[PDB]
Image (cartoon, rainbow, N blue to C red):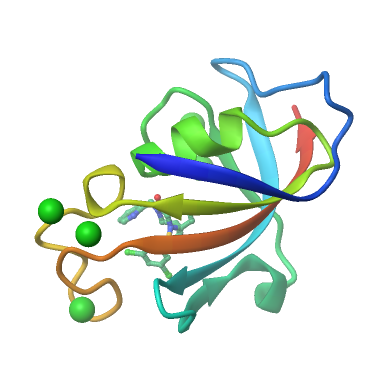
Length: 107
Ligand SMILES: C=C[C@H]1CN(Cc2ccccn2)C(=O)[C@@H]2CCC[C@H]1N2[S@](=O)c1cc(Cl)cc(Cl)c1
Ligand SMILES: [Cl-]
Ligand SMILES: [Cl-]
Ligand SMILES: [Cl-]
Ligand SMILES: [Cl-]
Ligand SMILES: [Cl-]
Ligand SMILES: [Cl-]
């Protein structure tokens, strides 16, 4: 599944809702901490629509349990990420993923 561990607090009250555009910054790491992607390095907030399944399951469920302004660590099992196959060239087989996510805004 996905485990969400708080890093810095949000408002404790405003959570993503189905159909909202969710705006975050993130860094993605393999289980051992090897960074593979970051919106921060691009200086480009990342947006996805909750419930559209355009991001992995661990994001759908993990970011939805964050409140606006929160920074949190999401630890995502392979079955909530890219599974047995992974995504060749960046996500290896059966990879547990760790994301450092900040929920910036809902629009
Ligand atoms: C590249 C941006 C997305 C990619 N997706 C959705 C996705 C779309 C198409 C193929 C694989 N995954 C995702 O669900 C997750 C979580 C949101 C942030 C990024 N990823 S991962 O960090 C990721 C980052 C990169 Cl550069 C490539 C891939 Cl295959 C996966
Ligand atoms: Cl979107
Ligand atoms: Cl999107
Ligand atoms: Cl969308
Ligand atoms: Cl790979
Ligand atoms: Cl297993
Ligand atoms: Cl595992």
